[PDB]
Image (cartoon, coloured by chain):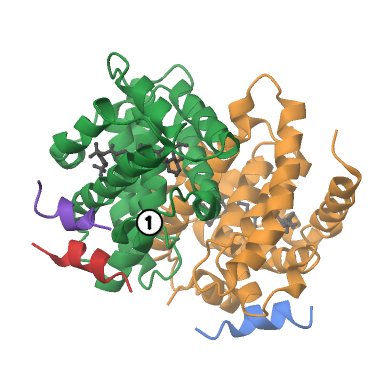
Chain colours: A green, B orange, C purple, D red, E blue
Amino acid sequence: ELTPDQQTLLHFIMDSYNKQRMPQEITNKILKEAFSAEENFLILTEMATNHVQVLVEFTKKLPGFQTLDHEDQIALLKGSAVEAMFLRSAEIFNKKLPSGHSDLLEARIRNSGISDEYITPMFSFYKSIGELKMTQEEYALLTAIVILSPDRQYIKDREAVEKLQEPLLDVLQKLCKIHQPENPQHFACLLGRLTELRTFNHHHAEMLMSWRVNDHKFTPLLCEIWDV
Amino acid sequence: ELTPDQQTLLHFIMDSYNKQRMPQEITNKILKEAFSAEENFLILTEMATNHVQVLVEFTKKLPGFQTLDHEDQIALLKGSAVEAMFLRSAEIFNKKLPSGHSDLLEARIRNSGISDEYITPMFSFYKSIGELKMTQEEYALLTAIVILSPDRQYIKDREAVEKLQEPLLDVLQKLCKIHQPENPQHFACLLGRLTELRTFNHHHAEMLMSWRVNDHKFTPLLCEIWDVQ
Amino acid sequence: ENALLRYLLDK
Amino acid sequence: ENALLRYLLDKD
Amino acid sequence: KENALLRYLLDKD
Ligand SMILES: CC[C@H]1[C@@H](O)[C@H]2[C@H]3CC[C@H]([C@H](C)CCC(=O)NS(=O)(=O)c4ccc(OC(F)(F)F)cc4)[C@@]3(C)CC[C@@H]2[C@@]2(C)CC[C@@H](O)[C@H](F)[C@@H]12
Ligand SMILES: CC[C@H]1[C@@H](O)[C@H]2[C@H]3CC[C@H]([C@H](C)CCC(=O)NS(=O)(=O)c4ccc(OC(F)(F)F)cc4)[C@@]3(C)CC[C@@H]2[C@@]2(C)CC[C@@H](O)[C@H](F)[C@@H]12
């Protein structure tokens, strides 16, 4: 199985992963609140907004992340943020998540003033992520791997970032082998989708120009991270 | 099948990729020179060196490579030479066992002063690229797709590099629909191999730091290209 | 009302 | 630029 | 840095 240094590291990442979850006050508006395009756009930008904060906290706690250059630090978080929201989306809409709570989120997302033209493929992709039957351990690592990407624009010390992603990859790869000896190209088919994640990055930029309701406004931190 | 524009693209890639192969004299030492760590080392450093030259000639002929910032072109060339030799390595050790060489190529690698710790991973991976059963057009593309990667450090204009890659990707992706329609996630298990290739880049650097043979320097162009010492 | 989350949410 | 994001990364 | 030989290969072929 995994080694003692790849198990401390595992254990740790999972903790920080599960550390924060959605605050009730948001989870209340998902169940018990107005079902207009407006308002849904409100719940979904509250949600998005919680999610970066929770991200920025998980990232901070990545082993050796705060060693890195503070300029690099921003560039990874700006770089990975949309990608982590997509990936957590994926996991969300497959999850053993119980009765109708995600059915509910799927239904709000579709009455929040986004076109079915953008909305249809992002679930269609979430479907295929799902087919690959990943564990929360797997989601947690890939999420780390995508944040600690050293190939991102404006990284000034690419070597420092890869000395951190490497373990995370080792660990994920091994656990792909442990989990799934059936077919042995499963690790590579994981990574391959991480590349696909990067494609949607610019699609996300685009659709944001069309995603306005009531003449409302995204929240400030959303304007920084998705640059709107 | 692919489209008329996707075929004029494929035809010009293929040609270059075949335009030049290893000089007869170098490949002849594999078969005829004394078999020692030292000798093998020099034989392989030579193939290396010549592969870089072949690589540069293959790239300049890529459609559109020269419209790029002459700087971003350097930056592509440097930040893919080690990976393209990876692409190439695998292909060689995956064909219909030439048996007139290739096997002795391997025999010289395990006896040329590289860790056994480092070597057996590498052939492990080169087999995994065989359990894709790629063709030469697919190896050729993947190559080309690796050189034209806008994710490379010190690229100024990525969107330019990004614009030249996607057609290459779509053709490699249409070739995978045809050759393996009975796995749609397969063109996605190529894109994973490309990330895997990067991790070996770092392995290949750390190994260099150990790989010495009774003095014996590397060729100057390898030291530039592999950032040796 | 989560000290940081409000303000962050305050458009 | 990214003063909010830098604050979240730097705050204790 | 420089990449002086790689530049020579890229320019005059
Ligand atoms: C058309 C599909 C949609 C959805 O996608 C949609 C969702 C999908 C679910 C998102 C939540 C914010 C998840 C929040 C969470 O899950 N918090 S959390 O506190 O539980 C938690 C955090 C992080 C975390 O990970 C970490 F620990 F940080 F590593 C773990 C838990 C979402 C509300 C975002 C908007 C997004 C959007 C409407 C927008 C435009 C497109 O972009 C999308 F396509 C499109
Ligand atoms: C432990 C595994 C080994 C091998 O890997 C080994 C080989 C593997 C085969 C290599 C040839 C140079 C290929 C010869 C060819 O193929 N030329 S060629 O002229 O036929 C041609 C060119 C390019 C081309 O493509 C283009 F068109 F240019 F794009 C097409 C044809 C190699 C001799 C390099 C050294 C390398 C090394 C010992 C050390 C570096 C480590 O990293 C490796 F691990 C390690």
Subunit of mark 1? Answer: A
Is residue B6 visible in the rendered image? The answer is: yes
In the image shown, does A55 or A109 lie closer to the viewer?
A109
Q: Quadrant of the C terminus of chain A?
A: bottom left
Quadrant in the rendering for residue A136: top left
Which quadrant would the N terminus of chain A be assigned to in this image?
top left
Closer to the camera in the image, B161 or A28: A28
Instruction: Kindly identify the residue that appears in the image at 41 percent across and 19 percent down.
Output: A181
* Between B66 and B142, the one nearer to me in the picture: B66
Residue in the image at 36% along x and 37% along y: A40
User: Is B204 positioned to the left or the right of B61 in the image?
Assistant: left
Q: Amino acid at mark 1?
A: Lys
- The vertical placement of B137 against A190, above or below, is below
Q: Is residue A219 above or below residue B53?
A: above
Q: Indicate the position of residue A200 as horizontal and vertical percent values.
A: 53, 46
On the question of residue A7 being in view, the answer is: no
Q: Which residue was labeled with disc 1?
A: A217
Above or below residue B214? Residue A146 is: above
